[PDB]
Length: 312
Length: 319
Ligand SMILES: [Cl-]
Ligand SMILES: [Zn+2]
Figure 1 (cartoon, rainbow over the protein chains, first blue to last red):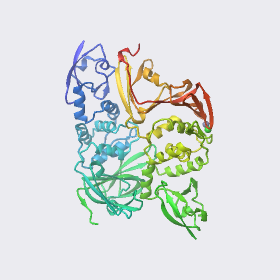
Figure 2: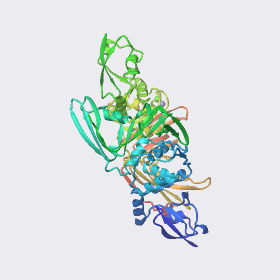
Figure 3: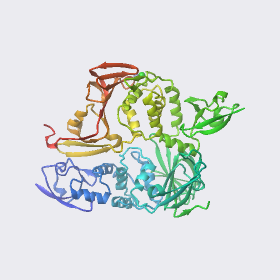
Figure 4: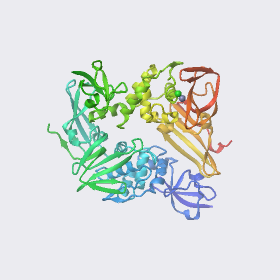
């Protein structure tokens, strides 16, 4: 009438639990999962002896273990993660030019170019759940990592994601504390004004795709009301993310790390990934295409960096 | 000869230009608009001097200004926004019971009840374009606000629209991040199954018009012969939107804030706005009608809210 099972929220700290065989797992634990499979509606079987089941945090011990692994206090995070994992566990994660991509399914193209981008930039995540899942994503088992991204971004499978918003969500769970960016906006109604940015804001800019033009100076509307020019004074980061509203942009080999292109119907479009190696490669899910240059509606371009100091 | 004019993409940053009267505006600016009207193939007049013209974001600086004002990156937005403005500026926006409505034109009835609804629920738009246009609409100048709605929804003037679909796009451009909804699904085999929604999904529901029935519990499908009950556990929002397919529904004074009624089918129909004050007012364009109760094919009901926590104990759910 009883079996011994183990319940967990992080698959690290296991918890011995006795369950009645006449009552389902849902009546005893609430929502319960056995390796991504929903077993809430199922009564415990003989073959479930000693197996490990995923459950939701419903006491002090499970909530603190879920907080130390996922770095979140959201009580619904694990459920939204299990809901996405039920789909991401079915996706194909082929190795494309040494990078782990995703075959297209349920508008996951923004997740693919984000996953392909993360494998080319230096970035260390703070939540242990994100670190462990990314390491496995490198090996072609990205089901846990994609379900975590969807949970952290609070997006469901099938929704159109934004690469810039997605990376921004991931950067806020990454160790970018030591990153620093120094900017200076020149004009005439103000003259000069220098600001310093730290963390996530130091590695992202919206308005220009060219990292070189960001150093030469871009024109922005300043509240002063003049022909204001913003230029990069100092950059201390392992990478930079340049983003802009989509227009026709020319990518050349060796001048960047990787980029993202957005095409199709704008409300519900499609993302592609362009990476720079010995030449330019376009990764569209599992499809690989190589060319010397690339012309298209680019939205995000990533560049490598260590320490920049302007000479102007 | 030459005249001086201003170009812009947001009507905030005005870029001075000198145009020759021998060539069209298109040859000098690209696609150009004057208060919504396409003047691309029109040559400048002497009376055009000093006027402000809309152009398409054809450089990086213009695309930055459009994104900071409209909060969109769709390159087709400004053109579609101007195409609608050339129609919405000719609409009449009457004031009905202290609320700005719209006179019937181009099937704008769905825009009218949405506009009247936005004047009664606590909502804060993120794009500065929507904030500015809303405040002008509250006064009586809703041409820009209506044109922005059509552009943000990818609907053209004349097309019959959906209020529930329209509010979704507008809520998507509003700060609903501190809005939370906790639900509970109770199946005899599944036990309890709680879920938490945030943002737009925390203030919209499709299945029932009654906020009380949502709290009492509604029947949702589990299998072809087995159903389960879903009820609201926790709601943190200034309002909620209860939507359901059109059905005869008794609206009573004091139980709701405002509601939308729809007569017709998928292909063609008409919207009316019901609002609760000291009594029920049916606003149909410029028409005003007063009645104690109201029965009709209601499709959307809006309720005020601040913080709600259920008093249901799940073991007693079916009592
Ligand atoms: Cl109408
Ligand atoms: Zn109508």
